[PDB]
Length: 223
Ligand SMILES: [Cl-]
Ligand SMILES: [Cl-]
Ligand SMILES: [Mg+2]
Image (cartoon, rainbow, N blue to C red; front, side):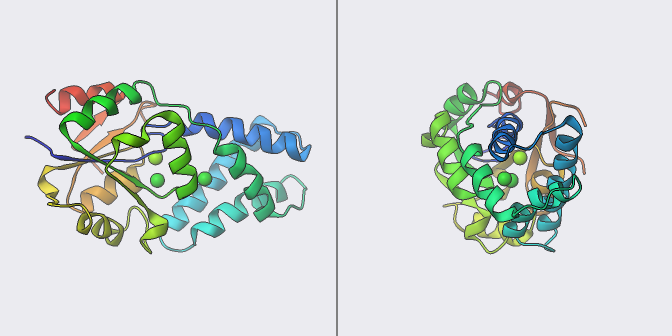
């Protein structure tokens, strides 16, 4: 077939969020003069993933996710913390990290010439615009669809409906979504009636395609 419209997730799809996060956590903890252990990093990631999942399922706001993750983590290690203040510091550090996924720039640069590209993301709009710009990816996308502007969030069908209504001459059948989240991107997109491409470099709901490297999309899209 011949897709015309490509919906990209941002974090761990085209930008290396793991890298950004690793640095921002270190800088947050340095700032707070709190030792950051490998165990603490592992617990952060379970806590953070659990909060985001709760948000995705509609049990929590995104503000709560971001403003309680650090207070919840530190509580388990004997520190009482202002979650909101720590998130403000963290956010400032995170926005400086604009590390790319291997081959992302080249890929997006080439695909822009033959497809219409859109961003679909639940991340903080200020954060996503800055990193997309600093990485060089920004100019290639026709529109940016952030959860915070919609009243909903990936994977919710109402988020994808908001997106579809706002893409001119939208055709589900000629639309591919590319993303790393099996639940947010792949299951969201499939339920919303779209083909899906699961970005899964670490080889962890059946997608139309599953890839290890962004460069595999050249073959999938026949170009
Ligand atoms: Cl997202
Ligand atoms: Cl975040
Ligand atoms: Mg992602």
